[PDB]
Image 1: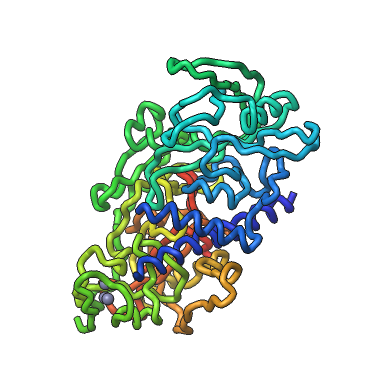
Image 2: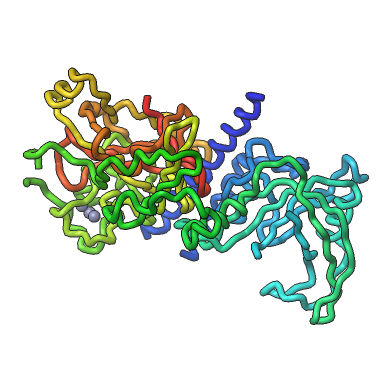
Length: 482
Ligand SMILES: [Zn+2]
Ligand SMILES: [Zn+2]
Ligand SMILES: [Zn+2]
């Protein structure tokens, strides 16, 4: 159905609001982490007060519309926002009301720690560190689990994993629906009674996200163990990036990406490249400096290097600035830092995916090619060559990024100045980086921002790519080429 698409869109907007709100609370406090979790919880409660949560009444059993298997989350409260799990410190979430059941409570969602069948231990009677301290009782969550076994209730499983990411200390991934097919009384070596439940996954679902996670990680540590064939080359960047760029092909013998000369940063025409002024933020850019004024009164990034909102042009600090490398206004000049993979595909010629988790608003890499003037572009274009026009990239799908107007009534969007559009062209037929293998899509998960750092010509800003949402590993990256 297309109502499915409508659900997915609603979820998209909800997540954009949540992450924007979090980031705002962080900017507010930092103007004056372990702060991450508290701010996440606050964002949650604020969204709750504004009636912005999904599945608020918990009356939904089984799939949450718009939330798909493999979706990743960074906080427990976030799961409450998306209606997946309503108890951020408890393993079992349950609904007292009755459909099947008879007003009898039934478990609708469980949180499972990482180490398909799951041997799940009931809750209750533990200390502050979760250590069993008394006999469990068949009440609340446990009784609800029992009842869900009895009534054959579809139970959502969300797996929690200590997983590398830049927003929190863990990753929560939705693994879909399981059924409880057995339950029993069991004893630990402590001697306390506990309840155990055997969970089995429902047949015919998409691959679990936790499997994809472990797979990606393994690709970072020992790729040949899971992919003994396919890897043509483990760095086509060929040491020109600070991280290796994988090249994978398990379909045929084509090795085209090898035949380009890798170019990590866009090459501007010789004889463009000095006079400009820098800020004096010797402890890093905060508020009220010159570079902020250059950015219409708002520094593009938060203190975690994350894009706050889209802008027509980003002025990063350069050599004229007295801020150190750790300054929050020096994001894209760091270059690629994520491990990416250019892989053969059928529907697209080649595609790009990330081995790492990518969070909403995070910088991925530059879109690097050979930049032309209008004369040079014209000459190559009269010969028949095809050129890329960065002005045609569309990020309009994610323009609500940073919008807090649904949470804060008094919110006004900071100015997005009307400037002349970029008009230069890029050739990527000879020299290019990983980003040039990114496929086209009307529903992109990557946005474009024009950035200046190394030079100060408005006519020739760099093309920098940012993750538009929380992208789990192995998800293909896409751009709207327009
Ligand atoms: Zn500054
Ligand atoms: Zn600075
Ligand atoms: Zn500066």
